[PDB]
Length: 152
Length: 152
Ligand SMILES: [Zn+2]
Ligand SMILES: [Zn+2]
Image (cartoon, rainbow over all chains, first blue to last red; front, side, top):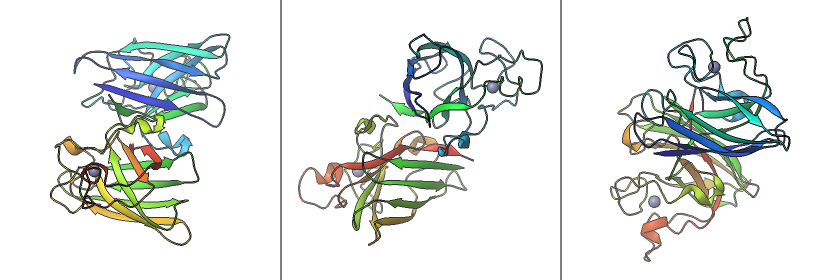
């Protein structure tokens, strides 16, 4: 099982993120490259809808099938789409390499048909002390997104 | 259950296609419009992979989970992703309104996460006489496509 996503936005952020899940209930490897990002941390999430009619805005909130509060990937309390942050180097490139066991490429937690979004700022992983933190992690605006599709 | 698709290409072709299915075992309504199409008939299909890393080229062939020959949407012998043709009027616009009961927004005929493609030439619905007909319907190149995503 494999998925893929082309990230595009109004600005210069763009990239290709690959998803792989060998076992139906195994972790998903998420890897790829994103360019045009400012050096530092950027929120990285799977949002609810694969709707790009109004750009990244129509993607809705973080995919949250269990109605839980926003958290970091390692947390028990977190949205299914909470993959944390990705880091861009001084050259504006983030060589993404994540492995997650909460998102899936099948079943109730499937992210295929939804939207991957890389955000403006760092995800505070829900430790910012306010409602925003436990909702979006204060990661800011959506710099680029794409709908997650089936791949071979 | 709903889905949506934003079609884009290297040329002027662009549009938005909607999908609706009130019953998991019922038919799927498909509607919207595509502009930039030369007046006439255009192949309209769901291709296997929702991979746009190489534009529409990486989408693969027509979604064909049952391994059948290419056909028209109303043919018993068809590819699940075979939606026939759409018609662009003199204003280079195709107003799409389709109802199909082979494709689904769930289950094994699920097209969510796959790619919708609008073609260059008309689809000869697989009655063209040559091999290429029972494979692609001779619909020519892919002018625009998009990954089908879950919509609110
Ligand atoms: Zn979240
Ligand atoms: Zn076909």
